[PDB]
Length: 83
Image (tube, rainbow, N blue to C red; front, side):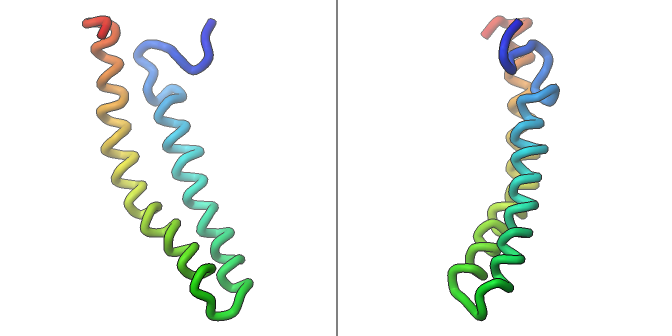
């Protein structure tokens, strides 16, 4: 068959890679950033690190949610319009 490339999929694996692995990665990264922040005393980088992942994560929930929609939609044209 093929590698990650099926019709009417989008969430079958595409979006899921940016949603599950993507967001799950952003959710576990701050966890590391957590054990890492408490690792070093009051530090600029460690704290900035968990936050850097935070601001990107909180926005992630909205972005990935607004990007996945148009993503699965474009495929709808590759079958009816062949795009």
